[PDB]
């Protein structure tokens, strides 16, 4: 629920996909 991990870390498919943040 935090949202930290699904792509916050820099390795997922959250909203970015290929960690572009």
Image (cartoon, rainbow, N blue to C red):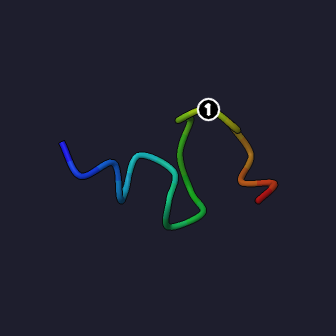
Residue at position x 53%, y 35% in the image:
14
Residue at position x 70%, y 38% in the image:
16
Query: Where does the image place residue 19, in percent across and percent down from the top left?
Result: 71, 54
Of helix, strand and loop, which one carries label 1?
loop
Query: Where does the image place residue 2, in percent across and percent down from the top left?
Result: 23, 52
Numbered label tally: 1
Asked if 9 appears above or below 17 in the picture, the reply is below
Asked if 11 appears above or below 3 in the picture, the reply is below
User: Going by the image, does 19 lie left or right of 11?
Assistant: right
Which residue lies most toward the right here? 20
Which residue lies most toward the front here? 2
User: Going by the image, does 17 lie left or right of 10?
Assistant: right
Pick whichever, 7 or 3, lies toward us. 3
Figure quadrant of residue 20: bottom right
User: Going by the image, does 17 lie left or right of 14?
Assistant: right
- In the rendered image, which quarter contains the C terminus? bottom right
Query: Where does the image place residue 3, in percent across and percent down from the top left?
Result: 33, 48
Residue at position x 60%, y 63% in the image:
10
- In the rendered image, which quarter contains the N terminus? top left
Asked if 14 appears above or below 8 in the picture, the reply is above
Which residue lies most toward the bottom here? 9
Q: Disc 1 marks which residue?
A: 15
Near mark 1 (Cα within 10 A), the count class, few <14, some 14-19 or many ≥20, is few
Residue at position x 51%, y 51% in the image:
7
Query: Where does the image place residue 6, in percent across and percent down from the top left?
Result: 41, 46
Asked if 3 appears above or below 11 in the picture, the reply is above
């Amino acid at each position: 629920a935090g949202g930290t991990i699904p792509x916050l870390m820099x390795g997922c498919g959250w909203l970015t996909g290929l960690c572009v943040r």
